[PDB]
Image 1 (cartoon, rainbow over the protein chains, first blue to last red):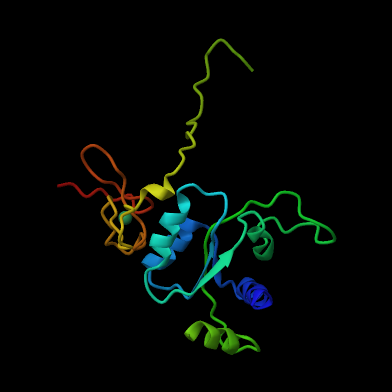
Image 2 (image 1 turned 45 degrees about the vertical axis):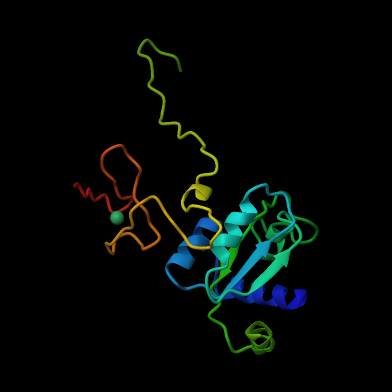
Length: 117
Length: 68
Ligand SMILES: [Zn+2]
C-alpha cells in the first residue's frame, strides 16, 4: 500500500489536492473538507502525538502510519530540487490533509475500497 | 551606517514555540475545546480565531473590532 500512497501523493500534487502544515490540516478539518489524513507515529515527538491523535480521530478519517517525520517530506516535495540525487535540506511534517479531487483513476477505486472497511 | 541620529530597529517578531499546540485543549476525550472565539464573518474563515488580549478580541485580515 506504500506504492499506492506514493501514487495518491503524486496525484494530490498534480491536482493541487494537498494542504501542507498541521495548522492547514486543522483549518481543513474545521472547514469540513478532509478526505485522507496521514500520520506519523513512534517518532521524535514528546507530546505532539496525543494532540494529533485527538485532532485526527474526529470523523470519517482513515489512518496511515509513517515511521519517520523527516522522510515524509520527500514524497511531498518540500525542497524538491536536484532530482538526480538527493535534495539538500527537507523538513519533516506531521500531518497533511489530502484534498484529492481525483476519484476516477487506476488505483483510486482500490484504495477507496481498502479504506471503506 | 551609524549616523548622528540613532535608527529605531524593526519589529523583531520573537519566535514563539508550541503555539499551534495551544489552540485546543487535550483531554481524555477526543473533542475540541478552543479558548478563542470564532470568526462569523466571511472575510476570515471558519478556522480563523481572534487575538487573546486583556480586554477585547481582534481579527486578523478582517481588521474588525468587536467590543462588548
Ligand atoms: Zn475576522
